[PDB]
Length: 227
Length: 284
Image (cartoon, rainbow over all chains, first blue to last red; front, side, top):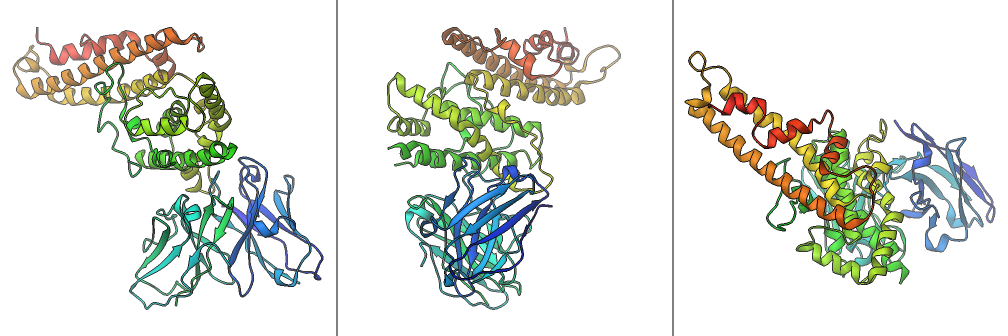
């Protein structure tokens, strides 16, 4: 039992600042990495930054390096992320997630419920997919050799309303609770998720994630929605 | 071979590839996938470290599977033995240095250098990185169960530098004490009891005489393996000039690692003069 609980919804005026909390419940914060990602209503998942605990020295995305500052408080067992110079398009839902056992890995495991705040991408996925109960479907991820070629790939099942959940990590491995019908593969410069026997619980948007050596950051794919 | 691990003792120690030493099957299977396909501070610090983490995470994953997902001491020692080999590869003390390992060495030399001052930079880089490599091997074991996680395996015990030949004698002695009861339990079933009224079954019973030739074949590989490994230890201990805290003979390494290690019986066991063997496989 390891929970992540974030603060309530906040509303800010364009240009102001906002600080979101993220508290751990059931394991010592002192060992986790505590990254952060957001998703606007229309747009997809985007990775902002995180605290690489194995080395300290938190890392951020590229066009965010002058707006985000991550703090911590060991007494309250929580993390804080502040965004300055809030633009109108920064309206989105912000998540805190960690890998829980990763040093240089980002197969996020424990996610928060999100925080509603009111004021493309290197990996390329198919714009949309559709299938019928009982058939094989194949969502594909394609990127350069500097992100997918030489690094592991992950997959996510994000149901709008709830937080994403880890589906596949290390390009081949599935967690405990993930059904057996899911499976991943990677070859050359493209990964692909496979759902053998599409059932009714596929009402989600699917993303691929990998580490880009040239960017030194976590990158997400555009997105893919099945029906 | 970064796919799965052969079952325990499916293959024994290889004393033939390099004549001066016996190599355990785990060393061959050590995952070095990313460490080979590598073909400027960032060349080593960031890139080579990531490549080594990707390999260490796999090794720590397949070793957990090798141990039937049991989180016990037998698993921690497989981590400890393998993490060290990763180090001897980086530090240029890999005793095997054959085949796919030759590519890794050339890769490291094109990064750090080739002279004496390169081993130091490589030995230094291992010290300032060995901890992170241990956290990588513990990846799968820690991801698997978010809660209820415990540091069964300890860090400093695994990242304590020790000559490779030492850590392999530790692994060998652990394999010996696990194998001996089995080869004896088989012997007991087919040779216990007396045949007529006072004679031993091995004198006439072929079924017992066959289990003896199996034990005779096994104990001979153990004696020979011990002979090679202990000679290779003497060659290294004599050439290193470091006191390594209380280890003089290779029998000390077993005393440290094994519980209730009676080297008197060990010498008797590997020389076919122990008690149980005479009662079961020696007629007169």
